[PDB]
Length: 296
Length: 296
Ligand SMILES: *[C@@H]1O[C@H](CO)[C@@H](O[C@@H]2O[C@H](CO)[C@@H](O)[C@H](O)[C@H]2NC(C)=O)[C@H](O)[C@H]1NC(C)=O
Ligand SMILES: *[C@@H]1O[C@H](CO)[C@@H](O[C@@H]2O[C@H](CO)[C@@H](O)[C@H](O)[C@H]2NC(C)=O)[C@H](O)[C@H]1NC(C)=O
Ligand SMILES: CCCCCCCC/C=C/CCCCCCCC(=O)OC[C@H](O)CO
Ligand SMILES: CCCCCCCC/C=C/CCCCCCCC(=O)OC[C@H](O)CO
Ligand SMILES: *C\C=C(C)/C=C/C=C(C)/C=C/C1=C(C)CCCC1(C)C
Ligand SMILES: *C\C=C(C)/C=C/C=C(C)/C=C/C1=C(C)CCCC1(C)C
Image (cartoon, rainbow over all chains, first blue to last red; front, side, top):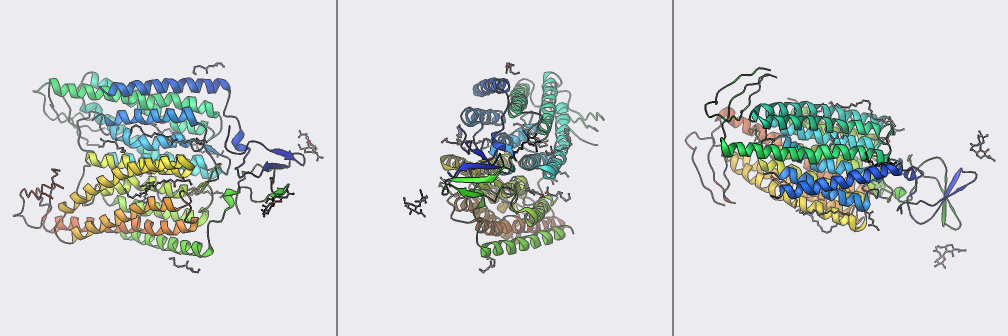
């Protein structure tokens, strides 16, 4: 079934490989097993469940809001490609140094990173503007993925360097993502909205933190995980990172917009000090509309 | 000098290739010449000249302004890698379907696309905020590059489809980039500043428009251009796209900031209709500060 050379003969007591002169690329490295049938079976189940959640989130969003639908849109196109060509090039890149690189995974990331990070910069959905910090988040995160993809394509000390360059960009991303969530928390009304923001923060840092961990564990790192093993781990954090996070996002947005429908846009001036930061706290009381320096 | 297999024997009248069983990947496709010595020589000269311009722009910017320096920073790191490992994997990816993909080129693009597009969204350097349109520009442009990179890694009708998907995202980018330049033109003071904005628009559309043209002409498309031929074409549009555009950008920014130093921030309300758009026209006269509906 492969469309590289899979048939060869060993000659001179396995010191020579002879192949048909049919123009196909050849490498033993490419033919290594992707894992056990149990790992594969587990991966095909989690993918269908991902397809189901992607399908239901989309129809649900069908009843502003563009970031959640798009991540579900990209996720459904991803599943149709997995279904037909999951291990066909270039869903997997089989390269000259013998590496298998899951370009399918890194491509989806590059596609939706702006969408997710714009949504990070718009949790309430009320903003029409994005600050300087949003721009640093996008630049740092895209650098991270570009260095990481380069690390996956490389070997030896070149892989180590590009991974370290990704980690430096990544730390800058995590640091600034943390400030956004802190501002969001003190912006939204006091009740359920702050539960959802707290939920989104946990989902975000755990699921995003797991990507560099799965890199180090996978064939791109120390080869602890098999390819199916890596797919299974990716499906779990994929469900958290995309479907669940966007679902919680849409829910938060609904709650905020309903607050404007009942109480109206009643802002405050919570001056944080987690520094000398400032925030417009939506409240349910018209009376409350003053400067509350809550130095953290 | 290659670190894939370069030594082989033809057997049974060229129907069989025999290779040392040394674990190296092998493909004839990878060994095709990259072009003539004249093409190579031309490419090495334009690269040094690019290194020189990248070096001088950086020192010059050394005497806010972060987008121009970064593009020169990424450009210098690019040249040191070209100098030592231009045709080593993964600066070029040699893949199982026989393709050579210049990952070096696509990586630089992904890295700086936010930087350039943020700078597009900040020509005057006075804005502290970015509108909804900036976000669509970044999402569309990163999609374009992801589809294009996928097209370069693919073959046959799969390459055609991903290229078309890139073109659809690309058209959305070009359309919205055009509106930004139109707003910028009617925002800046009447004199030299509008010459520079006009210069930046021409540089941008010509240099950005040439990338899909060089794709179609290169090994990733109809193979009209050789690899050195493609490098030469890339160096020319690289000089325009990065160094020259950022230099004109820094110059514009200086002019605008000097306007605030002499006349001060005197805005207007030029209501454009190229629709029902609005603009804050910086003027050199305190008197002029009214609504000028200039329906285009
Ligand atoms: C064919 O090459 C193989 C290399 O595997 C040789 O087999 C082994 O021989 C050495 C003895 O020098 C042992 O260390 C290994 O234990 C042997 N077996 C294996 C499975 O590795 C074999 O001797 C060679 N034959 C000739 C004629 O050179
Ligand atoms: C070895 O294979 C080659 C294939 O190139 C054969 O060479 C050619 O033979 C055919 C005649 O059937 C001609 O059409 C070509 O013009 C020949 N030359 C070349 C350069 O292509 C050759 O006949 C084969 N030998 C044997 C014993 O099968
Ligand atoms: C801020 C977010 C917090 C979470 C961040 C997770 C921290 C992971 C860092 C590990 C350093 C260890 C070195 C990593 C080098 C990776 C490259 C590699 O695997 O090298 C290939 C090998 O040398 C040839 O087979
Ligand atoms: C909006 C910006 C204006 C400028 C935009 C430029 C327009 C280029 C479009 C061409 C369509 C022609 C089809 C292109 C298909 C490309 C894929 C390809 O080369 O296919 C490989 C081939 O089939 C196997 O060798
Ligand atoms: C599809 C959805 C998401 C959220 C994908 C996220 C991917 C990452 C956060 C990747 C992060 C990396 C880091 C932090 C450093 C090493 C290289 C990586 C790209 C794996
Ligand atoms: C390094 C600096 C720049 C400005 C790089 C730009 C690259 C592009 C504009 C690429 C555009 C593409 C398009 C429009 C459609 C086909 C795929 C491409 C990625 C080549």
